[PDB]
Amino acid sequence: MDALQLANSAFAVDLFKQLCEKEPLGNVLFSPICLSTSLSLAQVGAKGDTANEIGQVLHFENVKDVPFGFQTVTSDVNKLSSFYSLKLIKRLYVDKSLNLSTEFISSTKRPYAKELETVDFKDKLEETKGQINNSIKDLTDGHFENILADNSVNDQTKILVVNAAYFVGKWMKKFPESETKECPFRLNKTDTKPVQMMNMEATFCMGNIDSINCKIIELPFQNKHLSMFILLPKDVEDESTGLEKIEKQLNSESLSQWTNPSTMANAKVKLSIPKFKVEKMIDPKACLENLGLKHIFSEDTSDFSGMSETKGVALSNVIHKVCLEITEDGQHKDELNADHPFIYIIRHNKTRNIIFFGKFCSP
Image 1 (cartoon, rainbow, N blue to C red):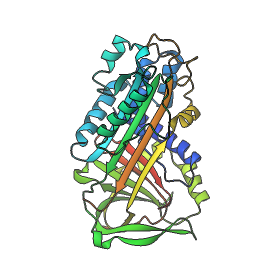
Image 2 (image 1 turned 120 degrees about the vertical axis):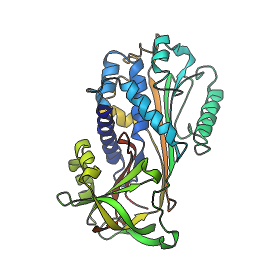
Image 3 (image 1 turned 180 degrees about the vertical axis):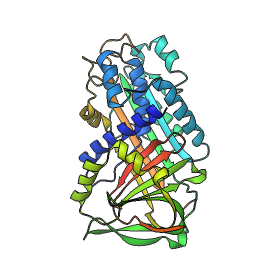
């Protein structure tokens, strides 16, 4: 569990850094827990170098019973769907010709409940595409109507990972709408872009790392099941400086320390954060390959013998789309004015797993 969360956060940072490299000025957002869950299911069906490469990239080296750890996180998180406007949908769609192993199905029935599905890519492509789109549409309460668009599924698709996640935030402490106003978001020391800036004064856990010149704040969502942590540089900087700080200072160990409330003090904070909605689709294949995942995607070299005796099977495509919407809806003294670029995570407080991981670079 603790071993698992640490694996998940380490992988989350690795992937985030890959995404940052790909889009340095972009508003990165992904759901690392979804990708870690999906890929751990694939690892159950893999063997040899395929299984070991997944484990290494996902940092599973020191984790015993990975599927049961995910069982618990998925359980916790599925209950949260009923309280929060939140869905984290993970599906592994496999073609009929895979003839899934019985041991694989029974091994994964409880830990990855509903996440594994057989479909007919080979002989019924357009029907299957409609079925997947519509199934994901209902699973995400109407939010993602066409998950398969701007990516491909084709009649040779063997295994398909779909992650689709959304969260419409509801704070523990609501922002007063009347104090939300348009401000120049400071892109860097000279350049500006307009943004709806939310404002309140309330008590929050806040950290204040002088050494890395960083303020961290915990902003709890209703009933404290999820919190957003904002890591905000104390001074506006050039984008090169900021991207170098991420590159050199951010690691899973440091992130965990910086965002640990045990290091944080209760403060009355004059708080300013942007009102924002971010929706991002990513192609993880390229990034996963960079991390070391080579055997996964090769029909010639992959060993998926734990799930299928069919030849030429591999992870065909990974789809990963996330939408996050942040609004007003909901004796130390300090200021947190996030009107310049910051990193944010949304943590499941119980397990400490990162649910969403992002960079806010511009409105």
